[PDB]
Image (cartoon, coloured by chain):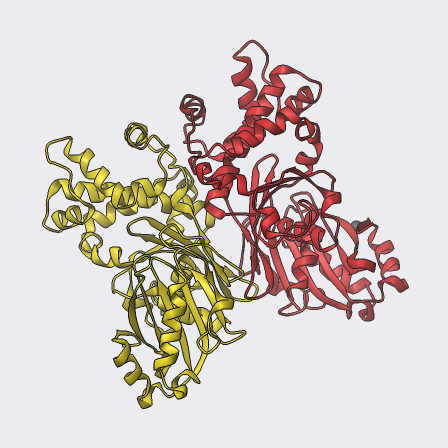
Chain colours: A red, B yellow
Amino acid sequence: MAMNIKELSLHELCEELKTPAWNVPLTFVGDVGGTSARMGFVREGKNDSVHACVTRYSMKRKDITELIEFFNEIIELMPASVIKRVKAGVINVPGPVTGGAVGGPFNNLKGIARLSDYPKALFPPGRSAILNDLEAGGFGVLAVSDAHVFSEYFGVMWEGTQWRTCEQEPAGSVIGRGRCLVLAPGTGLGSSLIYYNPMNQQHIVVPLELGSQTIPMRKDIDYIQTLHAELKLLPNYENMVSGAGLEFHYRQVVRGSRPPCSAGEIAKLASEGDANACKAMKKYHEYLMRVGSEASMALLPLTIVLVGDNIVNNAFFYRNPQNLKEMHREALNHEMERFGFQSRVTYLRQKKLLNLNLMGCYRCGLDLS
Amino acid sequence: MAMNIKELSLHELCEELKTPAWNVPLTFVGDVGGTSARMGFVREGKNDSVHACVTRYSMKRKDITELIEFFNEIIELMPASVIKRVKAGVINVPGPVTGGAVGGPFNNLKGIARLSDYPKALFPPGRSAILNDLEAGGFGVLAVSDAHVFSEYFGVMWEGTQWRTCEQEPAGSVIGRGRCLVLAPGTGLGSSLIYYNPMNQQHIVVPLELGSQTIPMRKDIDYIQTLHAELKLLPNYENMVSGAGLEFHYRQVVRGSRPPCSAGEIAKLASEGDANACKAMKKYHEYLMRVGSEASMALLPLTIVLVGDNIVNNAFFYRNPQNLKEMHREALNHEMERFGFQSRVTYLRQKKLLNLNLMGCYRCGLDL
Ligand code: NA
């Protein structure tokens, strides 16, 4: 396997790092969420394979500063001769970061993540970074491409007109040397743009906030105004493309004839062929494709990639050719499609689970050398 | 005088390049438009100063390949001693470019711009590129900052909350260690993002098409639908923020009471205190700030800079505090301003004429 993540106890992780396969350069990585963090070491294997060994920590104190205790424990327990092989240290955190060094504040954790407070043995000076979740996820998409297994983790929804001019390899086999917009439609709607800088031969990841933009209309002014009156706020993309959004779409389908359902309930009903829930899912994806059509114009991407557990878990929806035709039609529903802008773009979807954030911490550390 | 662009005849340019001040390394630059090109040489002076000398060429044949005849004429006329000093060659063209080497196709010009067809005396190997004009414009904003005279060329419209959190120097004194969204509201509406890579402190120019985005509403559904019915297209930002857009705003302000005027006429009447033309300019700037409020959220810029001759020529509008306060209010008219996102951003406007494209060709050549 090209992408390998083993989860162990701290004590077992220490035994694994003394084995001969681990007597190589290391990257220290950490994927920090609201409840737990998964931290450890990544190495290269054969044919650009990626091998990670990580341990889980509970964020017991609901305090981002507790990470420093975890880092100190790792350095205290591991032999200095193992930690000496660390060449880079990258974590992702569930909130905004500045200077790649100062993360927060956070919705569900107290305090600020400060790279200058982290131990230099795991975070070597000038070869370390803190990333936002979506920035790490974008670097994770690049990592999958670099490991030659894009076609294992991503499926082509449709090939856009630009692909064969810009690239030699088949669509979906590599990320491509063109801008890649990463969208993460889940509870909310994360976005990041993977740019290739010709001058530097570097890819970089630009975190965005596309989800918080005001939804522009098509022929849906009454539908937008319905949600406007409910929220008391002009709707943004995430308001239509979110759990809350899917709940809204389902309420607007059934018009009081059925009880209101959660996003989870609705997706389950859709998977079972319920006409109402399927219609709610079509409406959710109509607004997702609106983000896509407008960002296709604004950002001129070669590719749009839909990532996350939700996308993988909803594979039934993307495999259905009628749903795919309806999504493609909405992706092209833009006045600028008379010039071909929306049809230029190749759309892909994640089809296999992977911790993209852990892989992206690793991939980001490679550009720090 | 830290940034100096002088226009000369070809013969006077040849005489100038033989003077002692020009006996230094040179960059060959060219700003290619639909009707003319300005091309010439740039040198560094004292204190990171920039000095350029350029000539105007007519794009008589409306054919991008005519540039090669201009390049060959310059090489034939200049002494070998002058051409020997050229260490980089960068031009910008009004259309898409791939691999920094192949430009076009173009709306207003025939043919394809091919770097591989250009003479190596003006475009030395490893050191040459073709740029899209939006890219060149963003490199030009960086050039101004690098020459230490941002406060000469750009005025602060208002300072946002984020500036003082990552810069100690006054707002408008330098580009800043943050994303800069460049907007060029002129005949149309150009956009690029000068992205800031925190991990290596690198500014990277990323051309965009924000003008072609469908306009999201505020309390203006009727106004947008009036334009929709005229264009038979859902309005995009450029449709409201363009010469055509200003002519539209003036038509709607007067409600038939005056015949239509051109965009230039409207700006002139506004400068003279005509209430109708002033209201038309307010409406233009209201949609320009909508681009700003939405992009302030989507792209999280440190700064937004309004560039171009049109901005400099309309100085009177931005000098008026009532107009500036009404622009500030629209810039903050976003649901996400309840969290302070729009108040983060510093807005600046170009206040002195400068060919940013020619400066960007130079500054891009420094990154090669
Ligand atoms: Na553990």
Query: As drawn, which residue projects farthest toward the top?
Result: A257
> Residue A311: where, in percent of width, then height?
66, 35
> Residue A346: where, in percent of width, then height?
60, 42
Task: Indicate left or right for A64 with B152 as reference.
Answer: right
Q: Which of the 4 image quadrants contains residue B172?
A: bottom left
Query: As drawn, which residue projects farthest toward the bottom?
Result: B20
Task: Indicate left or right for A38 with A46 as reference.
Answer: left
Q: Which of the 4 image quadrants contains residue B223?
A: top left
Task: Indicate left or right for B183 with A307 as reference.
Answer: left
Kindly identify the residue that appears in the image at 38 percent across and 70 percent down: B69
Nearer to me, A10 or A222:
A222
For residue B343, say whether it is visible.
yes
Nearer to me, B173 or B24:
B24
Kindly identify the residue that appears in the image at 29 percent across and 79 percent down: B13
> Is residue A204 depicted above or below A324 in this figure?
below
**Count of all numbered marks drawn on residues in the image:** 0
For residue A244, say whether it is visible.
no
Kindly identify the residue that appears in the image at 65 percent across and 43 percent down: A34
> Is residue A224 depicted above or below A50 in this figure?
above
> Residue B256: where, in percent of width, then height?
13, 31
> Is residue A125 depicted above or below B229 in this figure?
below
- Quadrant of the image containing the N terminus of chain B: bottom left
> Residue B45: where, in percent of width, then height?
35, 82
